[PDB]
Amino acid sequence: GAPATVTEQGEDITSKKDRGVLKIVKRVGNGEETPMIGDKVYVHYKGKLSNGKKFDSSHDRNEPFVFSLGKGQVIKAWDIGVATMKKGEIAHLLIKPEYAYGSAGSLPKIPSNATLFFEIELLDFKGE
Ligand SMILES: COc1cc2cc(c1OC)O[C@H](C)CCn1cc(nn1)CCCCOC(=O)[C@@H]1CCCCN1C(=O)[C@H]2C1CCCCC1
Image 1 (cartoon, rainbow, N blue to C red):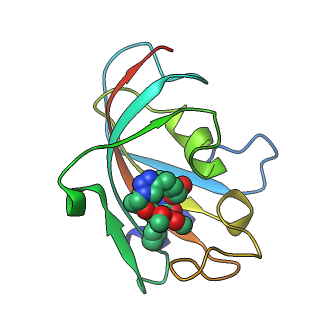
Image 2 (cartoon, helix red, strand yellow; image 1 turned 60 degrees about the horizontal axis):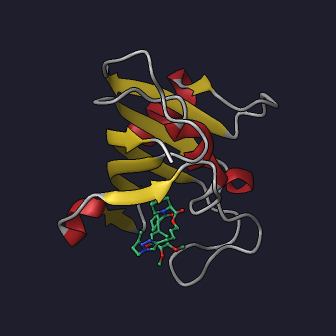
C-alpha cells in the first residue's frame, strides 16, 4: 500500500540522509515559494501508524489543521517535510520514530518506536 510505496520510491529529505523522512509528491502544487520557519501553515491531512493500526484526519474535525512552521508545534518530520511543499501539493510522508515520537512514544495514540505515514495537502501559508 501507500506506506510501502514510500519506502520503495520516496525521496530522503533528511539533512543527515538517514531515511528518517521519505516523501512522494502525489499531486503537484504551484508557486516558487515554499513555507519557511515562522509561517502559519494550513493543511488537510490523513495520518496513521504505518501498520494501519490507528488513524487520524483533519477532516474528522471538519477543519484544516493549522500550525506555525519550524516552531516544534508538530513533530520534526512535519517541520522538515512541509517546508518542501508548494501550495496545492499533496504529498506522502513516511517517518521513522527519530523524527516523530521516538522511543518514549506518546501513549495512548503513539507507541514506542512507531513509524508514521501521512498524506498532507498544503492549503496555504502566511508569513509571521
Ligand atoms: C500525539 O498527539 C497527537 C498526535 C496526532 C494528533 C493529535 C495528537 O494530540 C492528541 O491530535 C490532533 C491533531 C487533534 C488535537 N490536537 C493536537 C494538536 N493540535 N490539535 C497539537 C499536537 C499535535 C501533535 O501531532 C503531530 O505533531 C502530528 C503532525 C500534525 C498532525 C497530527 N500529528 C500526529 O502525530 C497525530 C497522530 C498521527 C498518527 C495516528 C495517531 C495520531
